[PDB]
Image: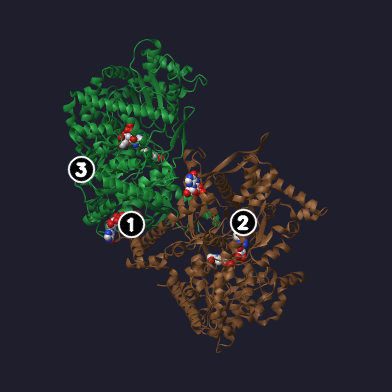
Chain colours: A green, B brown
Amino acid sequence: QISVRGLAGVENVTELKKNFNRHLHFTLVKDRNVATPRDYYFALAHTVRDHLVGRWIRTQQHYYEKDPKRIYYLSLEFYMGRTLQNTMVNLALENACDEATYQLGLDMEELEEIEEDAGLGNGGLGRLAACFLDSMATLGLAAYGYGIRYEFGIFNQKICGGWQMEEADDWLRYGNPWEKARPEFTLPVHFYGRVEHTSQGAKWVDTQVVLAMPYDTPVPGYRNNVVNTMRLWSAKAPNDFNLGYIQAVLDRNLAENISRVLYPNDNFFEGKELRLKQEYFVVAATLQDIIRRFKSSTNFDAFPDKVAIQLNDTHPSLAIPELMRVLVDLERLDWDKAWEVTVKTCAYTNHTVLPEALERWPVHLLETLLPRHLQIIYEINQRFLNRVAAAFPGDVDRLRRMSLVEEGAVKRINMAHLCIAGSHAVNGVARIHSEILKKTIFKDFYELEPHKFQNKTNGITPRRWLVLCNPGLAEIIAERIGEEYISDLDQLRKLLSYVDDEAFIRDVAKVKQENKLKFAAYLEREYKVHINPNSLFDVQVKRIHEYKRQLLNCLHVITLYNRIKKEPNKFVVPRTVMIGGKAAPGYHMAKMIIKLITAIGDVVNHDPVVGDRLRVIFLENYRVSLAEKVIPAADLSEQISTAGTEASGTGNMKFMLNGALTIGTMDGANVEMAEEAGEENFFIFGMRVEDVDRLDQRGYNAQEYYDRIPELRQIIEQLSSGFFSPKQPDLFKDIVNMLMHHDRFKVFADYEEYVKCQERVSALYKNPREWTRMVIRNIATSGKFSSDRTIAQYAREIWGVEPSRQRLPA
Amino acid sequence: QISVRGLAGVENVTELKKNFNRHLHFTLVKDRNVATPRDYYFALAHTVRDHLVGRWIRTQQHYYEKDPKRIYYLSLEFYMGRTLQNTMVNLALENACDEATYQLGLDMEELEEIEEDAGLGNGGLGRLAACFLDSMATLGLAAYGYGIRYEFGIFNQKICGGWQMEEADDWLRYGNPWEKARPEFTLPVHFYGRVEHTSQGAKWVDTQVVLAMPYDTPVPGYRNNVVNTMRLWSAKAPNDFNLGYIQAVLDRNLAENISRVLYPNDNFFEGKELRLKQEYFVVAATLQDIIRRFKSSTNFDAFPDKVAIQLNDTHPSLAIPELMRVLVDLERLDWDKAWEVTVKTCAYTNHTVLPEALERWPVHLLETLLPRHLQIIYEINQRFLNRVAAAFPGDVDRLRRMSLVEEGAVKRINMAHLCIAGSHAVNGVARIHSEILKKTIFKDFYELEPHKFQNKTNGITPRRWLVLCNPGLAEIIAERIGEEYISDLDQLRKLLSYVDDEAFIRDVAKVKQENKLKFAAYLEREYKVHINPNSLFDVQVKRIHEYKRQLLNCLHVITLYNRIKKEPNKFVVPRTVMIGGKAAPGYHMAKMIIKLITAIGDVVNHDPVVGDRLRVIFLENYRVSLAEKVIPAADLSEQISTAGTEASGTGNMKFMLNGALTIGTMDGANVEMAEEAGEENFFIFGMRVEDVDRLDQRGYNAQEYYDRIPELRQIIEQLSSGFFSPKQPDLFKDIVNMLMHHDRFKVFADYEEYVKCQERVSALYKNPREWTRMVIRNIATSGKFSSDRTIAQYAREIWGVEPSRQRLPA
Ligand SMILES: O=C(O)c1ccc(-c2ccc(-c3nnc([C@@H]4O[C@H](CO)[C@@H](O)[C@H](O)[C@H]4O)[nH]3)cc2)cc1
Ligand SMILES: O=C(O)c1ccc(-c2ccc(-c3nnc([C@@H]4O[C@H](CO)[C@@H](O)[C@H](O)[C@H]4O)[nH]3)cc2)cc1
Ligand SMILES: O=c1[nH]cnc2c1ncn2[C@@H]1O[C@H](COP(=O)(O)O)[C@@H](O)[C@H]1O
Ligand SMILES: O=c1[nH]cnc2c1ncn2[C@@H]1O[C@H](COP(=O)(O)O)[C@@H](O)[C@H]1O
Ligand SMILES: *Cc1c(COP(=O)(O)O)cnc(C)c1O
Ligand SMILES: *Cc1c(COP(=O)(O)O)cnc(C)c1O
């Protein structure tokens, strides 16, 4: 139908149809008279999977023969979403499958909606890992993603009475056709025990064994016939486990609980024992796999030439002492040689500066669970602090600040400090964040080893986040500049030549309008909600957190409501304000914010005087597959975190690529996005980082803003008095109290500038031609934010390998 | 190679080879350079499974169109064993697959050994269910087996220091290619709650829900293109279950524990709550499935014309009050109509008279777990006892004896009494057992309703238990009388014409000798044990229980040892004595017996004076796949239970079919086997049932036998003094104490007759020609013991359906 979806040749369509019917009969054991849409989805998924496997086997064979340097990306999270459509796009099968299914009397889009998201992540960090796997395959790198196969991913969110309720995400209920169990490659992982010192070094004995069973998922590159592997470990009890009889069998569940559920915290360190077990489990199993593959090509001098290990935050930081343990205790290398190998192999990416998000494990936990690792950590610390003392003699305070061991009521290990000491490269995820690392929290480390510190600005894959979710936009771009931009996003710069082209302006605006109609229809069908598709679609979708300032958006929404009630008969630009995202189950304030948003909607959406001029919608169960629907429909992207708190953001980049304008602070990657597009093509407001610092030095007093801004005072009075909660007048007192007395993120300090900037947005939206020209300037300069660019920089500057766009044979 | 294994035509062999390679590549995702034997097994299993599915779909379609009466066989156990070879035999693919795998450079027998047993049963009762499913499919009945998909089946037995150790039977570790998950047909099962009485009858409310997810396995008939279904339920938590957050997800394990593990008791009622939950779970899910299928063709008058439910012992007895509950509470039938329907639908098979094996559930358990069912049971009981009172006025003791409710310290429900009251037919499993039921434990019920009581003598499938496990014997029979006997075992009677045929005598003896060499080699390879293949193979394999009298075999073994030591230089017929079987983990005496057997072996097998004249071997991990190896190698079958205790036996029949002579008591089916073959062709000894009764009336005094039999006294002194346990002199004092003072099974009372009868066995074994002629007379008269005969009798006399040998189209 459209050119970017590939060819639908007669023989291909014919062969897909016969294999579809073969899988329906032989694989699913169904005849056509009793098959449901779910059966048809599975028949298609198996048909498409067959096209992967030849390429998957050939790719892994190629790597075994050529023996390139191997990249191991270790993460506790991979937020993959759905696989069917992505696979078709990357194999150029989308039009052929569409045609083949059409001829069988089926609508492929309907079948795509049946697939469960693989929701094995919380948000941005997990989704970055997914985009990176896509870019690594597309750039022909011999890369492996290693993680945990959680039985239950991020919870499904239901809203009941305006409150979030959590239910289990039973994503494997109907099976996962994309994975292949590899029980033959099962490996032991040890816990507890104690350390014996013999004449032949240390020995970790009396341990409890849990088995790690791998499941492999294929990761196809974009049209290059490369298929890499994501390997996810599942926990299994050994067969002699506890072996009255019946209870011993039932107690196998305790070992297997390790891979049961994803901890649903975003930017918050909770620190449960079960979580520590997850971290070690992934590290221990992965390192054995790495070493096995290295031996099948004992001289570990070449280890760093054949292996790179990238640590996605500190969550797999135990890789450092585990590698030391294996090399010293099992392979009998001397300490110094082992340390040299470890440092050259490992690299660490930091994703946050929020103090509450940093992992600091109590010593007593490590002592009980991983006593050998704690000994190795103490040794690392003492040798590291010996270097600090020689570089900065007499600076005793520096020694305390840089220690891996944190003193206090409870002694803790600072895992970030461990990662820095044991890695040859430490990077932040956006220029401003990387600078903040060097000036604030890692300042001491930067002064000792300036050469370690780098920036690698985040990106997103243009396959999922343009071609897949927004085919109409992809097509009109392709009509002008061809298809090469899909694996070379800098080519979007050519679109600047069409900024005064009337046909292109019309086409960009038409695609957006189609995306909005399609999303407005989706809302009516699945959720019984009616929205005006001519209104400005004002969208904030991301995890619910105080730093992201969903509350500042709420204040603006109530301001617009109060202005309408004050002057009912004045024209205002109609808006649909959409906010979506999950709160961690333990995060009370985040749950209260969700309730506030739905409470505002209850008043605004049923006021007859407002009409369809203002609607507030809480988008339920925000996840990767919902992002693919709402982002292409957005006009305005809300990226309004307090300057200094969002390390990068990636949602911001998704909206830029899909034809929304951005309102935001100079935070994270927003800064680089404005630099690429021009500040005149961005709605920037609020305090810069330096302004936040000056306000902290003087002391943030929220009362001052309350006293000087009548419109803000009115809102706080409405909240306190029960205007938005008539049956429970004091329902929002914790929100009011926080805003007035304990606001770490300075919501009131940015209120005035935000409202004024929002007025400029509305003024531009009244002139569609100029709105659309500004959009073209954003899309055209979004090329820097391809994850292909990000990964090429990791490859050359950290991993020491050269990317490639060359195709393997088909 | 051999004719009974079917044809290996060029096109079939070619097509199997290509599909084998297709599955290796596409299904297993392996190339040939890294494939292991396990991969090759799976590639073959998937190749063979493909041939089932067309037939499976067509059969189930045929049943939906014709709408025959449906037979539902409910069991807590299905002891299936391996499926690959059985499937090839029933589809006539064995030679073609052998040839196809040979051409690919693979040995099919080697690949068959990789398959795990489906060990979802304890012993005879579970294996009977498996044989019955095979015969039902072979006789073209529209039959469904319904049970539980246990995650862990009967434990794997290891012997360590001569003691049994249990380990978990993780049979699903590598996957099960034979099953198909059907999560689309998942059904709710309720527990706990309470009963509300409204004006609209009773209502069961406030319950906890567990989901039942079905897994379907194909059951092929013998060369008739019929493929029936075994449906096994797996337990799943609902998604709102317990919905802090993390613990609620982990607590899903409590619901799913229902289908976790088989209770490993044989002929012993343990009565744990988790076991009661298993019983209700299978019943509740199955009955909803039955009713759904009945509605898709509300007038329940025709229900018994379209449905038969057979209860495999009392384990699914809750089917009776569950059916009443559904018909009265949900469908709103009046009680009397519902009861009429229930009685005509249900039939009950009893498998034991041992008091400790009968299920008697405490009222408090039922009251808490299934309060509505307990109310229905009380109502059933009161109406039933009203009938007894009208038939036998004034007989108050009869009322107490026949009650469903048993009085005492704890009130209990007698489930056998429930089954009799709620079934139109009650059968025993061998003529002597069925008579015992009418004269002893169910005497009162027989006097009230004589028409209910039947016999259906057990049988075994000649597909698994001759063609599959003993191809050499099957072939030499087929050479003389053709192949028709495989589905018409009465045709073995024609072999009586060859009893004086010298070629046939030679061939029968040669097949046995080949089976013995092959088993002696198997022992050396897998277990490092060396046996003389010219010795008489004396075999007792069955679950370890006091009633089966493995201890009487032990006494004979020690008698032979002591006789050899007394007269070293006298000729005796060499024997290899093989005893195998599992003890329930809680059954202390059974575990002690295993230790005694290995202790006897430790003395006997290392005495230089004995030489290879006597060996005692404990066969480890006895299970269906080991039965298939050892039974064809046996010369002597030990079936030596105390008369009145083995309801039927089926191992006895397996040995008869495979060319062993039998030494046994007149117990269970042994009686009918001797009747068919002629008593002159059986080694019968010991007390009859009537002799046991006379001895019980007088009082069993074991001391009398000790005082009068010097050889028996010597053995007891050896046991007591520590001859068989030198480092632990009193190790066997519990065995000695039981034998002397508390022996319920009268081991000493049969000792003398047993030893004398064993001497007659040895005398016959010295004359190979006459031994072999007696064997031919046994094989030739074994036709009655086909499960095809058994099932035809259930069909005509209980279920009211006509069997058929007609083929469906291919
Ligand atoms: O249960 C636990 O103990 C536990 C659970 C989860 C976590 C956890 C999870 C995620 C994060 C986290 N830190 N930064 C992130 C996000 O990473 C994205 C990709 O670089 C950035 O674009 C975002 O700006 C940043 O906020 N996520 C931080 C901590 C920590 C502990
Ligand atoms: O855990 C529990 O509560 C529990 C577990 C298991 C059982 C249970 C299991 C099996 C049996 C049982 N009763 N007879 C049997 C056997 O059934 C065979 C087929 O008809 C006969 O050939 C045998 O002669 C007979 O011993 N098995 C009886 C009870 C009962 C309770
Ligand atoms: O010994 C070998 N011979 C041939 N190919 C091998 C061997 N070892 C690994 N390979 C290839 O490389 C892959 C190994 O996967 P891995 O062991 O997970 O790295 C296989 O799919 C093979 O194609
Ligand atoms: O509504 C129907 N139309 C056509 N075939 C049906 C229908 N319902 C059941 N069947 C057939 O009977 C089988 C039903 O399996 P069951 O529901 O487990 O008894 C299916 O495999 C179909 O072939
Ligand atoms: C991109 C994405 C995120 C990250 O969004 P931010 O605005 O950068 O926090 C979170 N969740 C989902 C489902 C995403 O697709
Ligand atoms: C046949 C069989 C049984 C029953 O044997 P009995 O001698 O009748 O108790 C038990 N277990 C297995 C594995 C069998 O094949």
Q: Which residue type carries mark 3?
A: Glu
x, y percent for residue A137: 26, 45
- Tell me the tag on residue A797: 3
Badge 3 and badge 2 in a common chain: no
Cα–Cα span, label 3 and label 2:
78 Å
Badge 1 and badge 2 in a common chain: yes
Label 1 packing within 10 angstroms: few (<14), some (14-19), many (20+): some
Residue under pointer 2: B799
Whether residue A382 is visible, yes or no, is no
Q: Name the image quarter holding the C terminus of chain B.
A: bottom left
Query: Judging from the image, what secondary structure is the residue with disc 1 in?
Result: helix
Chain identifier of the residue bearing label 3 in the image:
A
Badge 3 and badge 1 in a common chain: no
Q: Residue at x 69, y 68 (%)?
A: B742
x, y percent for residue B329: 64, 40
Query: Judging from the image, what secondary structure is the residue with disc 2 in?
Result: helix
- Tell me the tag on residue B22: 1
